[PDB]
Amino acid sequence: PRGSHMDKQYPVRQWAHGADLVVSQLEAQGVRQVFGIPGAKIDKVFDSLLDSSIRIIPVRHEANAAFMAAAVGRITGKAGVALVTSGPGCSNLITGMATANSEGDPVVALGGAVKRADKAKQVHQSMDTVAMFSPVTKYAIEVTAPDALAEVVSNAFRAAEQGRPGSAFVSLPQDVVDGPVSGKVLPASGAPQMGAAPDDAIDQVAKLIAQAKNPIFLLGLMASQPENSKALRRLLETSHIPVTSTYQAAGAVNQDNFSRFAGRVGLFNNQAGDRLLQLADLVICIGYSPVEYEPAMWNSGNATLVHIDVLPAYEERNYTPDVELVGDIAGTLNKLAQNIDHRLVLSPQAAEILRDRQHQRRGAQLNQFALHPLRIVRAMQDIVNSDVTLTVDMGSFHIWIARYLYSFRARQVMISNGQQTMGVALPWAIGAWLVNPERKVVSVSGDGGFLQSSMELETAVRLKANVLHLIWVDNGYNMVAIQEEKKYQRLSGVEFGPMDFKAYAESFGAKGFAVESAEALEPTLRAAMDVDGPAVVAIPVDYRDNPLLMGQLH
Amino acid sequence: PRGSHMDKQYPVRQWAHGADLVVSQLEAQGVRQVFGIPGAKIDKVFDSLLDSSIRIIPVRHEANAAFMAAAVGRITGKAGVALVTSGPGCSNLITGMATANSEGDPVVALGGAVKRADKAKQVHQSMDTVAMFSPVTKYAIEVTAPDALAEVVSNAFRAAEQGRPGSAFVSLPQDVVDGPVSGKVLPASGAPQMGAAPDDAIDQVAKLIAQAKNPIFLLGLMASQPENSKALRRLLETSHIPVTSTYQAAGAVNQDNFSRFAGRVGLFNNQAGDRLLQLADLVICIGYSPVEYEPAMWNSGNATLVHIDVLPAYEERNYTPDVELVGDIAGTLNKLAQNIDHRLVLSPQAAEILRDRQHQRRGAQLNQFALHPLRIVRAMQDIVNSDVTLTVDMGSFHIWIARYLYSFRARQVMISNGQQTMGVALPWAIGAWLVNPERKVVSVSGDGGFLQSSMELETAVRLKANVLHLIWVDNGYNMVAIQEEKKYQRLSGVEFGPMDFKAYAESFGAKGFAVESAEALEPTLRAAMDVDGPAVVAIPVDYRDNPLLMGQLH
Amino acid sequence: PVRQWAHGADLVVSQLEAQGVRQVFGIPGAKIDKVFDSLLDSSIRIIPVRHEANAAFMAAAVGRITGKAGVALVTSGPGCSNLITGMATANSEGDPVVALGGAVKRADKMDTVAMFSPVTKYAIEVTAPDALAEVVSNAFRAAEQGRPGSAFVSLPQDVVDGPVSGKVLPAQMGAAPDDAIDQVAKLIAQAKNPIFLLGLMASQPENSKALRRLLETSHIPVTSTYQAAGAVNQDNFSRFAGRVGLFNNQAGDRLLQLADLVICIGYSPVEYEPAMWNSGNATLVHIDVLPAYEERNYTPDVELVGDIAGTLNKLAQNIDHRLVLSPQAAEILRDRQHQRELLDRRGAQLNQFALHPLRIVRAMQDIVNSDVTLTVDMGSFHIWIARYLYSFRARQVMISNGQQTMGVALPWAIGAWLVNPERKVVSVSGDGGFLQSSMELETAVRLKANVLHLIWVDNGYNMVAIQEEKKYQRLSGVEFGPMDFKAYAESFGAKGFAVESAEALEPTLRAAMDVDGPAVVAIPVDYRDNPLLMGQLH
Ligand SMILES: Cc1ncc2c(n1)N[C@]1([C@@](C)(O)[C@](C)(O)C(=O)O)S[C@H](CCOP(=O)(O)OP(=O)(O)O)[C@H](C)N1C2
Ligand SMILES: Cc1ncc2c(n1)N[C@]1([C@@](C)(O)[C@](C)(O)C(=O)O)S[C@H](CCOP(=O)(O)OP(=O)(O)O)[C@H](C)N1C2
Ligand SMILES: Cc1ncc2c(n1)N[C@]1([C@@](C)(O)[C@](C)(O)C(=O)O)S[C@H](CCOP(=O)(O)OP(=O)(O)O)[C@H](C)N1C2
Ligand SMILES: [Mg+2]
Ligand SMILES: [Mg+2]
Ligand SMILES: [Mg+2]
Ligand SMILES: [Mg+2]
Ligand SMILES: [Mg+2]
Ligand SMILES: [Mg+2]
Ligand SMILES: [Mg+2]
Ligand SMILES: [Mg+2]
Ligand SMILES: [Mg+2]
């Protein structure tokens, strides 16, 4: 009957093992799989998952379990789950949990721990994981009372999925998950029934839209959630105000569904969105937090600033909103749309800025070897259609793809990377494929980022994941090298040796390719896409022109 | 003149870049190389190292920089150095720093950080690294004042190398290492001139040795340091008291130089050392901390307990020493040796226990496929001579090697692993080889542990490291599986797919081998040893008999 | 506007003015004396206290009444650490408090931020002079917004002394969605034993009118935690079931366990452990400014997050009919009426010496009318007053004390009086709690605060003694010596009163009330009957 009744499909049982209650709680959360590596302290949860519909997916390095979990979280909106053992099993997650928290990806990590009695000493894993995960999670707690077992797990998903999503860590002592517990599953509660910002405030902003002549919407992470899709589109059609998005909101609005989309901001200093922002007399931020794009780089201060989000702003020097609309975003945008009396008439400069953007949007006329980056971007465009997901690692290739991200027509793109973690592309792709295994996923990284997570190629083969991984090969850490060259005119620690990435992939049981010539790139990628399973393509790249592109950055 | 004079070979300069002072301080510490991966926030230290005798060694994953650094620290006694950039560059070190701290390996990690002005916000790397490293280091601090730059680095090496050694982390904001500083290098101070434990106390223990009839020495980490080698041997010869060692002291005393060595304790429940400890009426711990071997597993409480170490004991339930000798170990053992009036006369049981140990110390008469573990141990014994270093990863193979560690005659063995971190063997071997590049290093791991650090095979080829890596291949996480089988009679998350490890190694430019038959093992290892560079040998293993060996554990 | 400030302290003070700060409590020191100095050029009033802990107490009273954070200003080192207990008490009770604590120069860097984090909503140190106004503004925002709490800001000496470039930052939710209020209105109709459980936020002044309208159109019975002890009383709502959390014989507890629908307003599980009232056999509705802090025994079926006042008004508009009490509900409320009658006597205090507690309570009731504020310290007297809260007709009562800190009454009263100095404030404490903050009698005299302080004198820590007697039948560490509190109060320059006889307390309290300034009244009490009252506790 009630949510906390002692008689329901969620009965109050005498559980033989706390792990059984943990697994039942996961089922209530809608968890479909678990990523991680087992160990003695946590093997009972792995064991209990055998009697569950939840799928166990062993990875080869815990860090990639956190990466896969984040991809699951971003796509589905419900937290991806990592499951690791105590000690180095937990500490191997920290970078992944930070990357998830930075991007707003809901992730729950369940980490084993020594028996409670052994915490008062120095044993094989006397590791204070809560203290280590606290700085890089929304939520980190250890279950010290077996009664609070289901409560702690439920609160972890609640912290990860609600508000501005983030990562959550739960430490599970061995004796708690092995021993008996008395409790019940806590059914999952959705989002709060939040009200729109107050009418006196939305009318105030509506009056600013009329009085404004160069208004622009700045979309943040929360603007890209599905709950706000319909409301956001309805507001853009009735207002016709131009829009620009951070990379955490890179998918909220595409150029092909809204004519006045001004591109993505946060990376390049020559974007239509940037010019419209500095030109703007009214900026309305939707679902945006300053962390997504430092306000010091776009807020000139000569414009009225409106904040629309599920949480109050964290005021700062270059982000002191004059009006603050706090509440349900969808409800706020709907009420705001009701008070739009007329559609915007673009100013000459504003209109010219959008024209200049579309006029820009070389190429394939570049048979040089090694392949020029702009050529690789073109070949990627031809294979990444609306049915393919694209995951992008971190490096110089990342900047090239971001520069031409308007031209990719992918169903979804995972590229946003505030922490700038390398090695994310491949595990992101495996997680994304598991959500929609009927579709193709294309992951792209450098040779540096590739080897930090290439161990998961074995996981991809074992899963038969339909993932095509592209490696831009330069035998170095180029994105760092270019910075050293500009600053010091010499390189330090950015060069390493070559590899036979074709045979490397084949040793995992996957299909390997190596672009030997500029004419062989399209034939090779074409063949690699047609592979019904894991495939890797090594693409020698010539980064000589990188200094030209990097000068366009902030 | 004085250590802090403003006029000396360590002059007070106006440094153009804090990084220059950092590098000069490293030179004063005797640092020969630096392991890590560069980045924008820290690239000035990499740049400054170009003008230095210190060698830059790029790795492919930061975690392995911490592992290599630990090996350097254990062998030389001076801290190995890791150098990483901010954000995920630092968080990727945490597991390695914990493994170093647990084993007492001196390691200094220098991690980049955002500008000081950008710490008061959420930027690309607003990561509180000090809070994350504190639980797994002896020392973690961030340089906020450029004047304290050399002080902080000096104190990091001091914390790492002195007392019970450990890992230390220093966070270096970008503006501090890029901007100018005014300071001087701090010359390195050796160990304190400590005095022996008080005479009234050493005589008290000397009187206990006489009154004792089953005394035994329990050697800990500090007993294996070179400063105590001569004193320890002199005490064992004049006393002839039996000796047993933790694995952190596995090298302090070898069976071939002392007849009454009772093996290593901490892993197996059927060791001569264990029987002598439970039989003992007097246990003298030298350089030992309870963390090395839980006193609950060997201290029955029916024996007088003496503590000899550079630090006071941390009393606990099963470790309340009756006598406490605190001071310089070497000086304490020397004074104690002066008061030995006669050599011990072994008791019948004590003598019988040592006889039973030597009588034990199958084999090669096992042509079964896959190769029986005991056969692999024999083939390893034939190639690991006194000129070879042996590094051992974590897994079921680890238990087999530990069971027969008396039979290996290696110059040095790195096997101790309290945190039980997998992936340590290969990076340990690269670090060890760099200290003595004229010698051969043999590293052994499983297929699970191999892929967590196999990325460093590229580093080994690039370094031309004379490292032979052996993989016990079972296509699973066996050491975990055996625990699940005994506890639940079913497996969960411990199986993965096969790989062509021969071609895998060859893709890095290294020599690859695959033992196809039991008769080919010795021929293959023989050939792989004769390789003058990196080589990998895949060894299919049959773990069917593992349950028999694991029953001999605590 | 952006201004070129000569000293960071100038920007701090201007930011405080923008926040509406009327006074600052604290003690100056070298690291922070520039903020004290800058306050001379400000309309803000400097109120020196005699112990920093009491600055946090006074600040909390200002915060609770006005809704804008009270401000404490202390120097580095022990100046900050002396605040921790006060800041913890403010955070626990939901009182908005901003503490500005000095710190050594940045170049010379007690880790105060680490020490205040566990007992504050917000703790930060200003390391960049540019972010000075940002941090102060965010501190007030953290303290005053959402569920209010305490906030700490560490100000390095060089930051407030040196020049800064910045601007002042000038100083709001909508009602729950209509589709969600229609959902709740339908549940009230189908319900037959509904009850409101009021929490902290239901007691805020913004929700007073809306709450009354909801109770009038619904006539649903009400029970309150002690953080909401003032939102509703027995004399203004007939179906008030008392306050829950302290006594084991309250109508509110019985109605909650009987309820088939519980609507919590402004409530967090921390105010009253849900394990003691949520049986799980009822639909649970959560109405608050924040999402529910879910736990085992608190998984609401409906969650209304938004402006409480706007939500309750809209909900009251959709109530089609008034509740018809069930027999048990009516009987429970009847039993409370009979209980209140039994709690009353009337009795002629046969044991005149020492004065019986019930006699002191009546004498307090006669002087605490609707124009008087009452602050209550912690001790056995606290239980007595809590037992008879229904009978007090005070303008405001400060009694809620989850941390159970002693010494709060007097500084609470001084802070409360400063908000409305034209009214009388009555503070009551024990002899133990009195001496932990009695130093502020000098502040009261120096301020001419119209505060009447009552001391229940037993020469011991009674509330602990009674616990020891029940557990061990012997006392340990709960006895101390007597004091002549009349001369004690008079030595501060305040009026001192000593209840010499049982007939003189009302004459004395009457005379002490007629004092237009600080007054202290020592009241010898006979706690012999305490075991009878304490048996009524959980
Ligand atoms: C970072 C980290 N993450 C997780 C664990 C780990 N390190 N260490 C182990 C350990 C020692 O911790 C223990 C005993 O398995 C355990 O879980 O308690 S080793 C082990 C290594 C894989 O096995 P591998 O193939 O290499 O060896 P075989 O046994 O021969 O097959 C396993 C998965 N562990 C958990
Ligand atoms: C965990 C971690 N450790 C260290 C860094 C990292 N992640 N991210 C980068 C970054 C983005 O952080 C930045 C800009 O290079 C930097 O240092 O600031 S990416 C980069 C990845 C290697 O380059 P790769 O071969 O893959 O790509 P190419 O550029 O095409 O050659 C580099 C080494 N970084 C530092
Ligand atoms: C800071 C602090 N330090 C210590 C305690 C405290 N606060 N609070 C109390 C408390 C409520 O906490 C409890 C119930 O006594 C307890 O210990 O649990 S109050 C209480 C005050 C009783 O003495 P007092 O003379 O003031 O009142 P009478 O009862 O009339 O005599 C007692 C000393 N406490 C412990
Ligand atoms: Mg399953
Ligand atoms: Mg956190
Ligand atoms: Mg590269
Ligand atoms: Mg060099
Ligand atoms: Mg530490
Ligand atoms: Mg294996
Ligand atoms: Mg209030
Ligand atoms: Mg806090
Ligand atoms: Mg008292």
Image: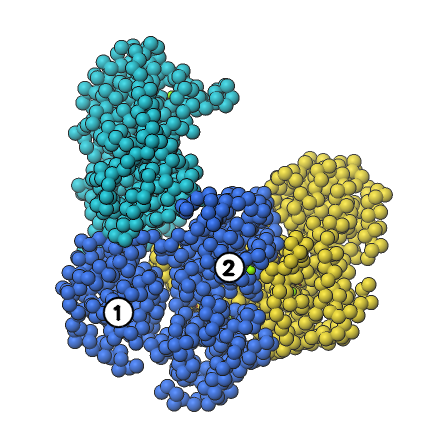
Chain colours: A blue, B yellow, C cyan
Q: Amino acid at mark 1?
A: Val
Q: Is residue A56 left or right of residue B112?
A: right
Residue drawn at x 68%, y 36% is B322
Q: Is residue B496 visible?
A: yes
Which residue is most to the left?
Answer: A211
In percent of width and height, residue C255 lies at 36, 34
In percent of width and height, residue A112 lies at 55, 53
Question: Residue C452's image quarter?
Answer: top left
Q: Is residue C441 visible?
A: no
Q: Mark 2 falls on what kind of element?
A: strand
Chain for numbered disc 2 = A
In percent of width and height, residue B361 lies at 82, 57
Q: Amino acid at mark 2?
A: Ala
**Camera-side residue: B50 or B118?**
B118
Query: Residue tagged by mark 1?
Result: A243
Query: Residue tagged by mark 2?
Result: A82
Q: Which mark is residue B185?
A: none
